[PDB]
Length: 59
Image 1 (cartoon, rainbow, N blue to C red):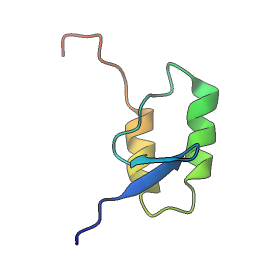
Image 2 (tube, rainbow, N blue to C red):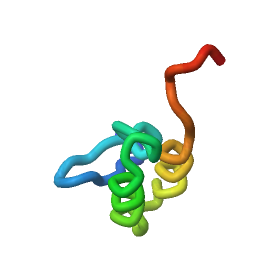
Image 3 (cartoon, one colour):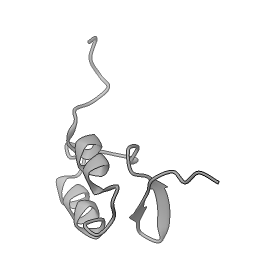
């Protein structure tokens, strides 16, 4: 089968592209999460997603 790219948070797995939250909500947690996924090939996907800004806006 094809494999999606998975990243780790806690003892849970999730798509690297789609983490549950971002930097603005909790900066410490986000960085910690990024550090945990340093080894993973998906890491850059995770960095991009974690780093981008929020939903409450028109554009």
